[PDB]
Length: 50
Length: 50
Length: 50
Image (cartoon, rainbow over all chains, first blue to last red; front, side):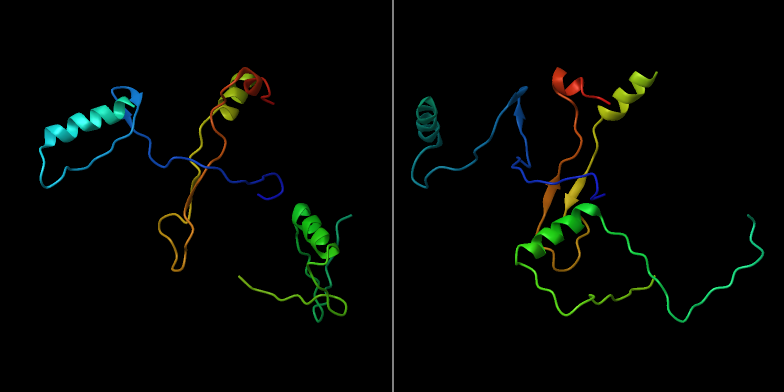
């Protein structure tokens, strides 16, 4: 098998995700012990706006 | 053309060994580059059976 | 018939495997995916079928 084959290295993603038919990725995490979830959601939306 | 019988000598034995050409050339180049070392003369050959 | 056979033979997906795959031997410390002949993606690639 070494008389007609070569070899090299590459970089590849071992896990591909899709959401609603488009490539996507997911971040999962909680909020602070002393604040509401909705405020964290709004701040995450503002951060994603950037 | 058809032989009558066969007479064989067994006290010494020949072993014909297959080397891939690319590995042979690569090792020759490595030895010519000073990375490898040679000792005395003919190299030692060991055997592993089935 | 020959053209169809050549296309079906050289434009097919092959499942290669994994370096350090399951079940590994005791002492392995390198695991990676293996990439091999994949589906052709361009006309220039597709026109080099032998």
